[PDB]
Amino acid sequence: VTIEDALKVVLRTALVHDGLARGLRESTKALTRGEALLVVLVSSVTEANIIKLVEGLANDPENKVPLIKVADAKQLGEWAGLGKIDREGNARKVVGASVVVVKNWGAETDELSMIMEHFS
Amino acid sequence: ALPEKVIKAYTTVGSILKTWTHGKLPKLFKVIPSLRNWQDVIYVTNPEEWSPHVVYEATKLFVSNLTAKESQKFINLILLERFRDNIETSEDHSLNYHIYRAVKKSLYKPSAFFKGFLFPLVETGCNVREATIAGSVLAKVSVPALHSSAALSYLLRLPFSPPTTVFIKILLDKKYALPYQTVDDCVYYFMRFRILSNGEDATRVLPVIWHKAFLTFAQRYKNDITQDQRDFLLETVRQRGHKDIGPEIRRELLAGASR
Amino acid sequence: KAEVMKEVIAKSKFYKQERQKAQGIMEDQIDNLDDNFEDVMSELMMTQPKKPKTDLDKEYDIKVKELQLDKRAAPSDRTKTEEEKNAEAEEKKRELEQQRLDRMNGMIELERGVEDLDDGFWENSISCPRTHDALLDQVKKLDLDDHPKIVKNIIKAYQPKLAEGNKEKLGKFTAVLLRHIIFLSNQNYLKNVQSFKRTQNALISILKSLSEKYNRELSEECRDYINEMQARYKKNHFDALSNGDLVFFSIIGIL
Amino acid sequence: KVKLAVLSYYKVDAEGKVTKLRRECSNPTCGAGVFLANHKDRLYCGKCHSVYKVNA
RNA sequence: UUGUUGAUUUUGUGGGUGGUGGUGCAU
């Protein structure tokens, strides 16, 4: 089980309990409130700001939140459930998500332990 | 208890709302959703005494400002009870136009609407007249395919009652792109009424609304069921088919292709 | 009766004045309330209270996401009986035939008449080619039998639903297609008459489908060709006339 | 429409320290994360519609 | 897109619907 595959189910489970803050605005609102348990950030964000200002908030001394690095925004949005399923079943009209923040895991899965163990 | 000055001011709010018909609502009333104890603040405004105009604008104020979780109580505790009270107490058992509009706006939030009106009502002794009026709001208003499909799956799993069958027919009439799992749930619902061991549902007398819903399902989702599912439904109409509606359901079912 | 009417009018005016007075009292109450808004809100904020979801609530959220994952069915309409379809088809045929007879007898659809006109006349990936040349460049490297293949692909690639303005692009393409149909006829085709026959009729069929939706665009191009050829006849006489002209006229009879 | 307004609300220094450039609403229901709109004469909450003085 | 909000809407192309409609009739 690769780390990326572990996150794919974890984000899926977090969706099922309304535990994801999707978007830059919802992400930062979650981080400022201390409600963020995990932050997933995209590498290819064109504006160097969005990387810095998410990183600084997550690395705050009062509330340190683990950070993950994702290659493409489009695939993160697919994990965030933005994309739509086709007649074939493949995702379509998928909307890229620069930042996704987990508020509630929902269910305890072995894949969550792997991610937490990776960070520890 | 709220501050005595606050109570007196909001007592004046309620008196305004009782006869309010047009204009600007009181500013104090407009800020209720922002308040944490809005339920207590709403209690002193006498929601039962709200004029139909206030109910519409109060609904226009709250589901927009309150969270999805908080809207559901405003939906469930006030506009549902007012919806039932107006129908029961009216001479012709009709619903006021402004309350009717208020139900539409509450539908703007589907999850709260389903969980504050539809599921509570059908699970709390809904009557045919209540189902008809509420179905018309559901029929006329655009609902997301996603939220409706889950709502349809709910009503199908509930115990059979004619008022629930109306809502099942309304959603089927909407012609939404139902997910295949929802289609299977629709089939299973009509499966359970065939005589086989089976529950008493097999022997229950079936009203026309049940068959009209079964015709709508056949007319629309015939191309989205498996051959095995089709054969089982063809057995249902054999055992429980109506005199006149039964042949057409057979005609619609037989002309469809398997998925 | 008059006295009863006057009392009715007086009563209606009396009730109207009461409603206006009630409206005035209400606006004063609202205005006084707004003035006291800040004091009431200050104390309420001071008394603001300090900071499990149901099983029916847990199941809904589980269902919604599963439905999001799940594929959706396409909707269908009720199948009309063969008798109803024939009756509707017969009814449409009757309406169209009756319209033709009316148009024959002098009915004009702007339902004006021919006599109205005769007042004052005597006294005085895939690229959609907006022009005829553009279509040739796209189909320059393709064979004669391949024109229908590319032409239909252009229509498919630019259907009205795909994007805004595709109607206009197809409308212009309808004019472009007609010139292509006429253009090919002008070109020599004695070598491969059979292949030319397999493209010439096929393009006309596509033009017929386009004309059904873009008759206005086709009509404008058709009138331009009539004007252009007339000008060519003014200077070249029969030398202007070509096979494409003879082909051109037939297509109007078709379309 | 305003694009990336959220980027403007808070500033980052070269060390990664994040500082908030706008005041947050004190209404308990709004809680943290609700930023007041800065007008010339007042601070306005878009959620509660409450009005605060700029220098209060 | 809402009034701050988060995909509930907006846009373009197709498109089913008379329906909180009445009135009588047959337990």
Image (spheres, rainbow, N blue to C red):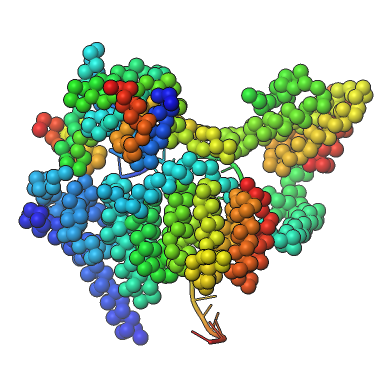
Residue C102 coordinates in the image, percent (x, y): 77, 57
Q: Residue drawn at (18%, 30%), measured in percent from left and top?
A: D23
Residue D45 appears left or right of D56: right
B145 or C200: nearer the viewer: B145
Image quadrant holding the N terminus of chain A, namely top left
Residue with the most extreme left position: B4
Q: Residue drawn at (27%, 64%), measured in percent from left and top?
A: B51
Residue B199 coordinates in the image, percent (x, y): 49, 66
Residue with the most extreme front position: B197
C11 or C219: nearer the viewer: C219
Q: Residue drawn at (22%, 69%), measured in percent from left and top?
A: C18
Residue D13 coordinates in the image, percent (x, y): 23, 15
Q: Is residue C40 above or below residue B133?
A: above
Q: Is residue B2 above or below residue D28?
A: below
> Can residue B219 be seen here?
no
Occupied quadrant, residue A114: top left
B89 or B172: nearer the viewer: B172
Q: Is residue C119 above or below residue C167?
A: below
